[PDB]
Length: 46
Ligand SMILES: [Zn+2]
Image (cartoon, rainbow, N blue to C red; front, side, top):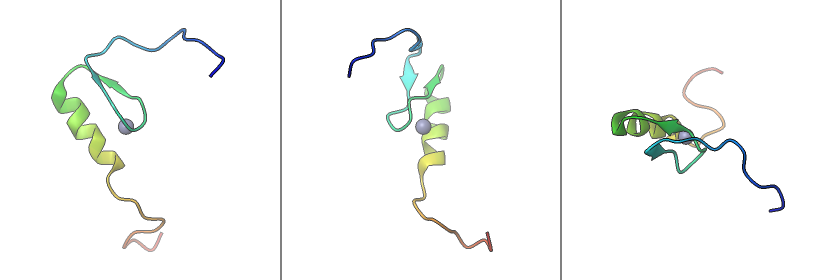
């Protein structure tokens, strides 16, 4: 950790997985879902 900080963001809700910011608790909760599912290939032919 050598670099500092320049543009972080000012949001009450933040993702503890990637670092996305939101304004409403619903936006974050609805986002954290996108993370769900840890598989290289789903039921779709892909
Ligand atoms: Zn995220």
